[PDB]
Image (tube, rainbow, N blue to C red; front, side, top):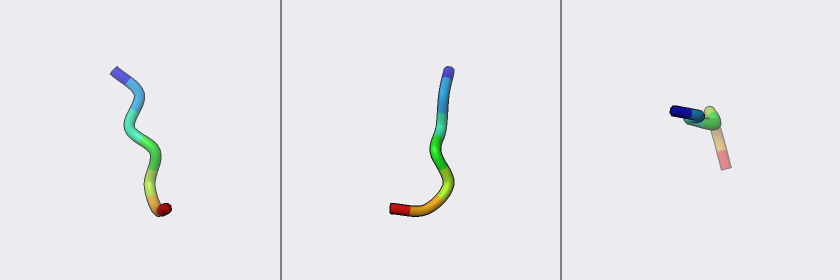
Length: 7
């Protein structure tokens, strides 16, 4: 699953 690193 795709986890993005920092908002």
